[PDB]
């Protein structure tokens, strides 16, 4: 099933056997049933699957998912909706269904409309739902201030009296689309995909959600705590459901003072709280609906960048269009680092190109009107590359709210490609 | 070339998988990689060694092991140990030995047991017992002495020594027993290749290389060879065309190697396999079995580099810089496999690499340039401690090729 990449005389037959054993081993591990495995031993197997290419992991994902369908008697299931009320009608029709029922084959029927191809109607239906779930009138999701086209949970969702039930429904629909192997135009924030994967956010995630709070954190990290006229404690204010409250980051955080040894830890904890604190119940509802269909441990083989690609698909990126609409600061278009950069980017496969777009823009969503219409925090903001004048042993940094790449003056092409390629991959949970 | 991309993938796959299996606190069958037990032959040495010792403990778990005394004389350890242990049962041999030297001070039993194993391993090879003899080519490696029949009770002794080697493995205690590569193949039930003769009968090997490379009409000369078993000479039938040569060379080499010692081996293997199941030991290669019994050596590469000779190559040749870079990048097991590949053993000479011994006396490690096409592996000739190294185009290619050459077993590039 799974495929691997690709001497004279007696050595050729020796190599082909060597080559076949390696493939046999890989395939046997990936074909092996994992349903006897607990979460601990399964996570160990994930440390191996995680290193494989995206398409291999997607293929393993779909294999294991179908294995979870054993013991099910799948039926065709009708979803009756009105073209004017698709979202609320679909909620009524599906939100009380069981998880097992949701694995049935949906066929949509619009009230009193001419019978069309069921397959296309399902595609049409998904398209409408993915759009309406982000409609402000339901107050479930809101755009991030930084990246504009990405969404996360609206903390003021309690205006809608049924929101918790609706968040569970929306989580169910996202999982159902993945299950049905149908793409959605739902583009969430990087941090939101982390929530699904059960990963903590970094302070860098704050930049596109709450810009000024992010800056305060960077200042705290880069300077001594004594340079502040105020003291800090392991506690922060959170406004859940319109009710403000001071929650402790760690067990006695209100009496614990923020020292230099505590800074990195403080920043880590406070960001987690601010990001998920005002939305913890809406999020828990969403994840309940999601994990009902797609187990958490199973989706955890993907990285936050890849999960988006799983849900929304792999895009085709017109690099010429991007290059035509790139601005340069300190660098010029003909600077050696820039020529290397474009050569490196073109040398990336489809997945890594997408991961790069995610890395600098905050999403894999390509603007319909081309990269001349790339949106940022302050309006239309073209992709821009700045020279990083610090030492050349750091990775390229990004600031997605400006669609900005900070590129050090690397000494060689081999170094630039290697460093850039590392930067676009998943980051660690390290506090620094 | 697409082949090098595959080798690059394969090493990544090797490194990742094995590293996970090393951190594992589970048995391999109980864990998530349980499917691999059927492909245990392909994993790294230490991983197979962990599996080996775990499986060994699991199969005897139903046994109630007690402490067992062995009474010997410090001056007569070998023959006394034969008396105390050679008629004992396999289950008795799986008990915990504690040694008592006749009329000597009671010491730490763990330390005293390590001293008893080191002394018996040195005495197995004493010519006075006429059980083993050194190979002419590699000098420091041993195999069965065909003239073992001088003592008529020898088959009983071959079984005893086989038992002691296995017992040492069972007890997880290392021995200073260094056999020939061919001998380890015998333990694993593997056939020898014509290349193996080079260190056993140099002149015969030359005849075989000539026969293989040239036409049969260039000789002037049947599936039979002379064997001197038990001092009694005989021409034994193996089963001579150009089409049959492949077959002829294979059979005759088997015969010259195993013909005069076939019963002595069967006795040794009987003794060995009583303690250690054959299927379990067969997960190792001929190279690896030695490392299991004798341990992984630590190699001072600086000492080796200081005593390396170069022919056609110079010390500053780019392939030589790559070579040392490749060797340094190898883990302990692969470094050992390299030492085995070019010298014929993993035993580091006590007097340093400046005293490396060869067929015709003292011979330092030497690297020659192989001027033939660069699509072949590095070749070795262990009786000269010689590495034949092609002028490889890149470091990545040289390293990949060297790694394949030192891991090669008689079943190909790693066991099939």
Image (cartoon, coloured by chain):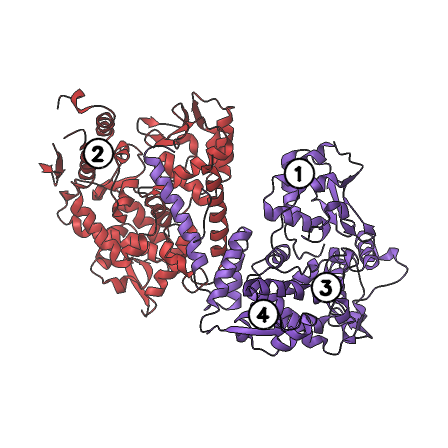
Chain colours: A purple, B red
Which tag is nearer the camera, tag 2 or tag 4? 4
Q: Residue at x 38, y 40 (%)?
A: A15
Give B382 or A111, whichever is nearer the viewer.
A111
Give B332 or A355, whichever is nearer the viewer.
A355
Image position of B307 (left or right of B412): right
Ranked by sequence position, the earlier of labels 1 and 3 is: 3
Q: CA distance from mark 4 to mark 1?
A: 50 Å
Contact check, label 3 and label 4, Cβ < 8 Å: no
Contact check, label 2 and label 1, Cβ < 8 Å: no
Indicate the secondary structure of the residue bearing disc 2. helix
Co-location on one chain, circles 3 and 2: no
- Residue tagged 4: A108
Co-location on one chain, circles 2 and 1: no
- Which circle marks residue A416 in the picture? 1
Residue B197: quadrant of the picture: top left
Which tag is nearer the camera, tag 4 or tag 1? 4
Co-location on one chain, circles 2 and 4: no
Q: Badge 3: few (under 14), some or many (20 or more) residues near its Cα, within 10 Å?
A: many
x, y percentage for residue B154? Answer: 17, 48
Indicate the secondary structure of the residue bearing disc 1. helix
- Which circle marks residue B246 in the picture? 2
Question: What's the chain of the residue with tag 3?
Answer: A
Question: What's the chain of the residue with tag 2?
Answer: B
Which tag is nearer the camera, tag 1 or tag 3? 3
Q: Taking the image as drawn, is residue B44 in sight?
A: no
- Residue tagged 3: A152
User: Relative to B188, is A289 above or below?
Assistant: below
Residue B345: quadrant of the picture: top left
Q: Residue at x 56, y 77 (%)?
A: A98
């Amino acid at each position: 099933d799974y495929d691997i990449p690709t001497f004279q005389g007696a050595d050729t037959q020796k190599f082909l056997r060597f080559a076949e054993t390696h493939r046999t081993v890989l395939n046997q591990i990936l074909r092996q049933s994992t349903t006897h495995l607990a979460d601990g031993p399964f996570a160990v197997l994930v440390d191996y699957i995680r290193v494989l290419d995206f398409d291999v992991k997607r293929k393993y994902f779909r294999q294991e998912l179908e294995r979870l369908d054993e013991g099910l008697r799948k039926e065709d299931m009708a979803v009756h909706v009105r073209r004017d009320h698709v979202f609320e009608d679909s909620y009524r029709e599906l939100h009380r269904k069981s998880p097992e029922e949701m694995k049935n084959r949906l066929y949509i029927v619009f009230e009193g409309e001419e019978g069309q191809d069921a397959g296309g109607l399902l595609r049409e239906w998904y398209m409408i739902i993915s759009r309406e779930m982000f409609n402000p009138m339901y107050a479930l999701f809101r755009t991030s201030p930084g990246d504009r086209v990405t969404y996360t949970i609206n903390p003021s969702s309690h205006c809608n009296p049924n929101h918790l039930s609706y968040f569970k429904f929306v989580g169910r629909i996202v999982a159902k689309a993945v299950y049905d192997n149908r793409l959605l135009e739902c583009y969430f924030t990087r941090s939101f995909y982390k929530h699904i994967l059960g990963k903590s956010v970094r302070y860098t995630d704050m930049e596109s959600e709450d810009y000024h709070f992010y800056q305060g954190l960077v200042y705290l990290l880069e300077n001594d705590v004594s340079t502040l006229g105020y003291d800090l404690t392991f506690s922060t204010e959170v406004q859940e459901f319109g009710v403000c409250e001071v929650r402790d980051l760690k067990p006695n955080g209100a009496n614990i003072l923020v020292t230099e040894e505590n800074k990195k830890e403080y920043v880590h904890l406070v960001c987690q709280m601010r990001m998920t604190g005002a939305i913890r119940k809406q999020l828990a509802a969403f994840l309940e609906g999601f994990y009902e269909i797609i187990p958490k441990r199973l989706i955890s083989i993907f990285t936050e960048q890849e999960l988006e690609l799983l849900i929304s698909g792999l895009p085709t990126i017109d690099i010429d269009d991007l290059k035509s609409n790139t601005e340069y600061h300190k660098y010029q278009s003909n600077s050696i680092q820039i020529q290397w950069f474009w050569r490196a980017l073109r040398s990336f496969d489809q997945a890594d190109r997408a991961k790069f777009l995610q890395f600098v823009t905050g999403t894999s969503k390509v603007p319909l009107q081309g990269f001349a219409a790339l949106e940022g925090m302050n309006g239309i903001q073209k992709f821009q590359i700045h020279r990083d004048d610090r030492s050349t042993d750091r990775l390229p940094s990004a600031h997605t709210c400006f669609n900005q790449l900070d590129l050090p003056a690397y000494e060689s092409f081999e170094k630039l490609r290697h460093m850039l390629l590392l930067a676009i991959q998943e980051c660690s949970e390290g506090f620094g």
